[PDB]
Image 1 (spheres, protein in one colour):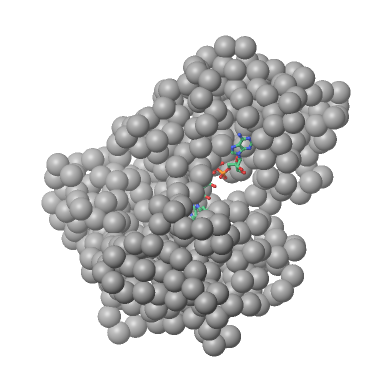
Image 2 (cartoon, protein in one colour):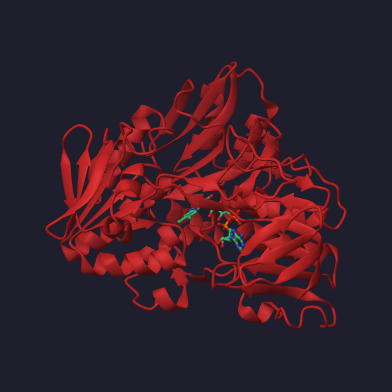
Length: 479
Ligand SMILES: Cc1cc2nc3c(=O)[nH]c(=O)nc-3n(C[C@H](O)[C@H](O)[C@H](O)COP(=O)(O)OP(=O)(O)OC[C@H]3O[C@@H](n4cnc5c(N)ncnc54)[C@H](O)[C@@H]3O)c2cc1C
């Protein structure tokens, strides 16, 4: 196509949400998604979670996973039949959504409302969304290593990485994960379970004192490290990689403190950089504090260019300028971007949530500014039988926790197995709650949103914690 009315760059979560938002507000709209990957839009969270807890050899082909409750779901947002071909898109009655797979936008000419693809073709647009997501960080130690080291290092991001790494876990004796964050720890538990059944080894190493140690308070970071160790994973905290080489066919990791780790394959999960390469020819601002395209309240980066998802550095209604790596944010900001591309002129006021499941038994949710260097008030309780991701998925029918929590924010609230197993952690700044972590507490994110939006100087967080830990039959009106 040489001209399209709506052009979405990137075919991930934010792009799909915007495409559907445009079609709802502008029925008959013609929307083209350009996607460098071969697959139609799909969600990422199952790649590190339910797709590993199957023992079904066919999921690498069907990309249908069993949710924790046993209900199957496609990783794809919509089947192919939902889309029209790019060739038909200009002509077909009542418009549609087409995806040009296997094509990368390599240049964006803001001034001329035009993109250029890797195959040399050019497309002009009336409205454009940048939904390019991010690019995984590597380690300099792996960068300096040889081609073989790099060929045996997985930056875990996409379906292709699930497929290749799942095969490796069936075939090798030792896999090492570098990175202690949520994704690394999800993979550690996933691989850990596979290795326990096979008799093989999984190592996880990171520089913090314990898993998710930059986010969780020390008590709960250490508990998480022991949970991962009970899955059979050798967890090595306080580990700084100095070099990686090959010796006798195996990868040899040398840590700064002198320890060595011999392993067969490496998975690095040490974060990402927003993909801002299309800023290179001008017209688009970038953020240096956090990364990403700087956008205004309506998610605009230029007169007819919007940005959504991981690539956007947006103005958080509570926290100011920030970027997130949240499925929830990609969905909500993508939808809003699509609305503003059809003239809604609405600000992005959503408080994005995050969640991580380490398995059916352990999950976390996070909202706002969740930094372990802030003072935290943790209020903990014994877990009941329903305080785990599997029960939450059984109650709601989805494992996509932003869907079971919903995007909404509570408006009014009415109040009519050997130690701690859940709790709420309040992150304080200026005597105010600026972030919350929920540990095995589900269906209360709307309440966490309300507490953070109120921003009052709370005494008796002992009492507020009861809204998360204790009260069951709360009657709440959501918005
Ligand atoms: C393994 C994994 C597990 C996750 N688990 C969770 C979880 O449990 N909870 C949670 O809240 N979040 C989770 N996340 C984060 C969440 O998936 C992301 O926030 C979400 O994918 C962001 O969507 P996006 O559309 O902004 O970016 P993406 O979904 O990455 O989409 C970007 C797409 O655009 C393509 N692209 C980039 N540049 C170009 C270009 N120039 N031309 C064409 N195409 C281009 C990319 O190849 C990619 O397909 C997880 C992420 C990963 C990788």
